[PDB]
Image (tube, rainbow, N blue to C red; front, side, top):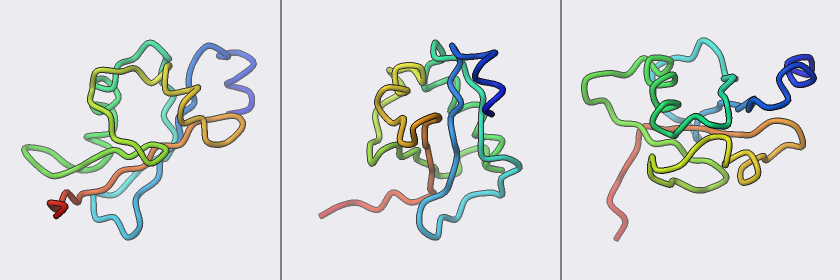
Length: 100
């Protein structure tokens, strides 16, 4: 990570975690290296299989307490959900109840 920065200072070291008591597939790693130009549609792909989900499972990414559509890019999120002073933080869950 620290070394991946000096060499790839233009990339985006995103972090991964689950909501409180989440219930999605297992996880092999919690840190993806994606370029800032990638769109939310591309990232949703590299995690999909990482969440052991497919067909029509349920899932929703929450970043910095937000849930924007796939009309954005991780690179732009860098300045938004950087969370820690080095990498960014993104978690996900399998719930979607209907607010009242």
